[PDB]
Image 1 (cartoon, helix red, strand yellow):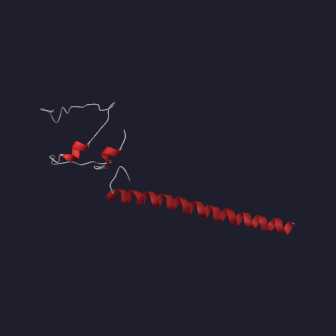
Image 2: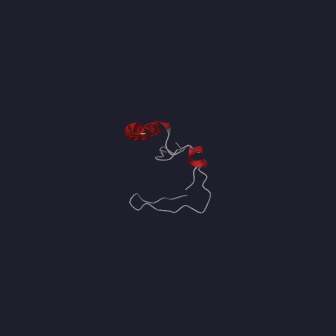
Image 3: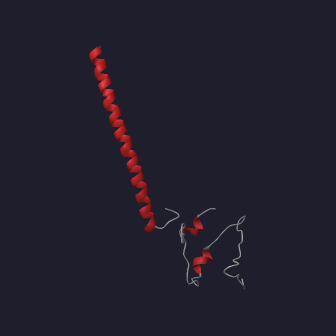
Length: 49
Length: 49
């Protein structure tokens, strides 16, 4: 924001947003898969109990 | 100043150990070309280096 004027700051911020959003989506997908695995494990534990 | 250097033998100077006030740079619009890349032309007075 300080170094560059809005004209190219817009594209810079867009690139940063795209990268961060991709990272968040990857993290959320990994978390969902892990949560499904843990749900399966918890169901097995509940059945054993 | 009164004289400058040649294009090939461009004179290099080190600026530091002082307070930089670029108010005169844009106050006197006597320069045909005035372009800043990677730094805001107007925010030059609100930066540290």
